[PDB]
């Protein structure tokens, strides 16, 4: 007879058998329960880059609420973005963050999450009018996602008061 | 002495003891962590059925974002819905989907979830004005939920640009 | 040789080794999966207290959707709130709830969650105009959170139709 062996996330050390727990995901308070890691509200500025229908950049003030392995993004723009077409792509690369939090892992999506486009709420003012769209993002790599949204009209224009609301599973 | 026996989700095969993991819920990367299953953004059309305060139907364009065991619904209507009263019930039965994704399990709520009404965001235009409500749905069975919302006024009318935003735990 | 010992959330009773599961977080259906606890939609009234930029109180009609260890709050006000400044703090203490649900644990945030400010969506009408803000709350203790939001203008005024939308991890 072979004895008993323990496969991850089960482990054994000095006769004690344990469940190894990601504290951002789970903990025990006797029974197996939700995360024990402290939540963070991160505040930083993110320079987004127009990558299609714009060669412009725009500063976003970002509040990243990290709770368990959910990071929720609340972004607001200062400035006008120059658009050239009826659709624009705005790229969000982790290198274009100033500040940059130490828990950078809270801004990288899981491999599971990265596999699909995800919903992004977009609003902005163009020609004094408030536009609002159900847009979509997709990660191109683990550090970079691009959102795609309508500009409100055609040709060259300036969109202002850009808000972005979305979230990722990390 | 009886020995040791392992209760689900613990299991033993050839001396190796494991935690069986639903990959839509959890995985191990050494420690027990969040889901490893790939996210999906599903796109299909859903014919909703007025079931009270309407005998009409309306085509919805649905984006179902499946991430872990969360499915988030973003629906937008093409067409007018005929209403007859100040409140309407709109039924969403899985059989009235065209396309219909192969991972249909992503559109069935958990028994836990099904036990309560859940929040649904509803908006639409009636008489040129944009209405918006915090509405509620409830599953009648595991395949069928009905949302209940105000129509914006009284008697016969046509509501347009119907949006529905909600999510289910599957 | 010492034998094998089982650390929480693993446990052993009469030779049977188990994973103890918080049913609000997890269950087994063979593999380890999401919560099995029934969801609740709670409905109660909550008297909020102006604690800075107001010495007033305001009745909120609250719908608390409890699903797993997520509680989502949908609040709507009846009445005017008297404000005195350009920013207001509104306190939500569990003692000021009437009704008060028996599953009060669904309205206490986790120690993890409590550690950070969290996003709160606020809207209201002032001077006939509809204001809307991305606001923030923070728990001062496990029973009491305070939201902080702009009033829409300055000096004494009355804000009406106050809505509050937020959620907590419990």
Image: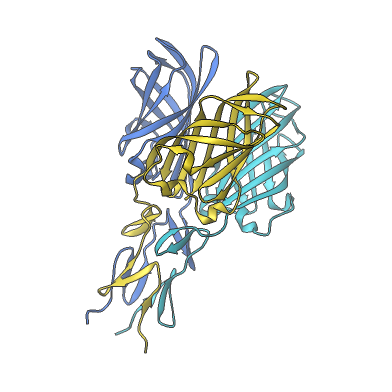
Chain colours: A blue, B yellow, C cyan
Is any atom of residue C68 visible in this view?
Answer: no
Residue C94, x across and y down, in percent = 69, 52
Question: What residue sits 59% from the left and 29% below the top?
Answer: B123
- Give the residue drawn at x 72%, y 39%: C50
Q: Which residue ends up furthest to the top in the rendered image?
A: A155
Q: Nearer the viewer, residue A165 or B148?
A: B148
Q: Residue furthest front?
A: B55
Residue C53 in picture, x, y percent from top left:
71, 34
In this picture, is C76 found above or below A69? above
- The percent coordinates of residue B113 (x first, y second) are 54, 52
Residue B115 is drawn in which quadrant? bottom right
- Of all residues, the one furthest to the bottom in this rendering is B1
Name the one closer to the observer, B33 or B88: B88
Question: Where is C22 relative to B156, above or below?
Answer: below
Quadrant in which residue A7 is drawn: bottom left
Horizontal side of residue C134 vs B7, given as left or right: right
Q: Would you say residue A78 is visible in this rendering?
A: yes
The picture places residue A20, in percent across and down from the top left corner, at: 36, 63
- B14 or C166, nearer to the observer: B14
Q: Splitting the image into 4 quarters, where does residue A87 fall?
A: top left
Residue furthest out toward the left: A1
User: The N terminus of chain B appears in which quarter of the rendering?
Assistant: bottom left
* Above/below status of C110 relative to C126: below
- Is C89 displayed left or right of B64 in the figure? right
């Amino acid at each position: 007879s072979h004895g008993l062996s323990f496969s991850p996330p089960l482990s054994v050390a000095d006769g004690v058998v344990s469940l190894d727990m990601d504290p951002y995901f789970c903990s025990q308070r006797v029974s197996l329960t939700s995360y024990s890691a402290e939540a963070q509200l991160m505040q930083f500025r993110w320079m987004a880059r127009g990558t299609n229908g714009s060669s412009d950049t725009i500063d976003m003030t970002v509040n990243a609420h990290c709770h368990g392995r959910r990071t929720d993004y609340m972004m607001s723009s200062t400035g006008n973005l120059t658009v050239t077409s009826n659709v624009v792509l705005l790229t969000f690369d982790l290198s274009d963050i100033t500040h940059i939090p130490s828990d950078l892992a809270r801004l990288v999506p899981s491999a599971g999450f990265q596999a699909a486009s995800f919903p992004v709420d977009v609003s902005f003012t163009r020609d004094s009018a408030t536009h609002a769209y159900q847009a979509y993002g997709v990660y191109s790599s683990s550090r970079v996602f691009t959102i795609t949204f309508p500009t409100g009209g055609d040709g060259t224009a300036n969109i202002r008061s850009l808000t972005v609301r979305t979230g990722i599973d990390t």
